[PDB]
Length: 187
Length: 173
Image (cartoon, rainbow over all chains, first blue to last red):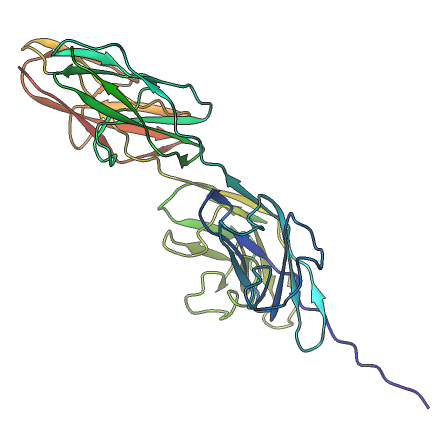
């Protein structure tokens, strides 16, 4: 007598892509092209069963289908090296994936901004702010930032005849902070 | 052996080409090698073609920067073979720059035009809207003898890719 043994094959290695250039607060998408059943995601929090528990529901790291979505309020919304495991729900076979580096960029703070002292009607004012490495600067006249006045670090605005305010946006590595502000008084 | 037109400005077409003379050509890009993409062997599947070359237009979902590799498929025997890895760079088009003027200027005076400093950029300021007449390549040039209202157009080219021209207006008191 002799016994035969069926051996189940593993699913293929998954190719993972992601929207890796993320400004903090937005949603992180992790996606395989493959068509595997049970999808297990491993992030910077590790592969501990204290996190990877329930296989479905609202567990962002365990889903049905080959893609997931980590919102900015989730405790797995973390920069670092991510890897996916495909689980065959019929045979129990499992397979790995390529490592993905994901960068969630901080939002810079609202910058301080400064004025000159009070200025005579029709005069000019230099506006100024903090130097920030990697930053692009924009100074706006409108509170809703639709009207731009300058992109200089510390621009001079001419012909100020009445009390006027300016709004400042500092964008670092693609992420824009909430605008700060200045006020030019008129003597 | 795969070659490609790897220095691409976004919007143009990406050519991936083998010298070899194999039959069924399978391309693997940054989207992976998943059968959810690599499906139909012909038709309009840009990653599966007949012949040893393909063309990925700028509207395709495989128009991606990254490491590409080709597989040659023998349509008679089923035998398959690999290829050298190709790094392909599709450069973004910079945005249209903001540009600024001085206040209104007296007839025959001069005006300094200015814009944003962009790393890796080459600057060109033009007098004509169609950009055929160039005035300066300075970051913030001064244009003399302005006697009437006149506009300028600005092109910022980064790593070889030119954005759509921005503009300024010099008013005359």
